[PDB]
Image (cartoon, rainbow, N blue to C red; front, side, top):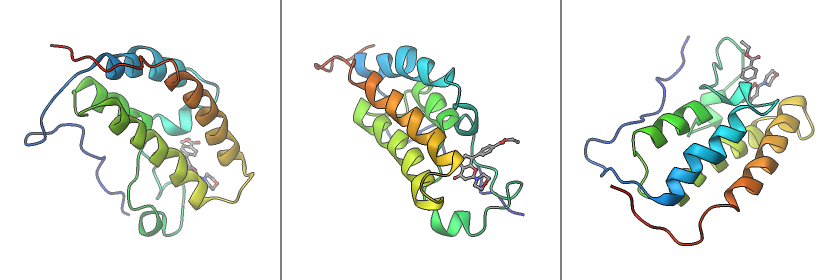
Length: 131
Ligand SMILES: CCOC(=O)c1ccc(-c2csc3c(=O)cc(N4CCOCC4)oc23)cc1
């Protein structure tokens, strides 16, 4: 068709780790985002073939979505919280560079992003490890 396989969520070489900030991201930030009115387009990888998105994978070199992010959180895939935050920003900016400003999907991403920036500002200022 063809869609690339979902992004990796497990790191054999890359070391596993957990912090109170990654914990807050999973148990609070992502839980709030997941039930937003506009979460559903971002809950799984973009099926660009079924959606007939021309050149989507030529233009979007790093596909990203909240289902991948959630599983990476559940797999301690991230070293720290800022790494998780980068995947969220990649998901939002993917949508902004691919679509006309002000389109429906862009409005949905913008509203999710606005909620996301609000919740990540509740993150503990100090990072502390977890077993
Ligand atoms: C089977 C039903 O699922 C959906 O309705 C669905 C799922 C994911 C997306 C989505 C996520 S990012 C993104 C993008 O960057 C651009 C497009 N477009 C643009 C051209 O109009 C059409 C959707 O869609 C998406 C959109 C709809």
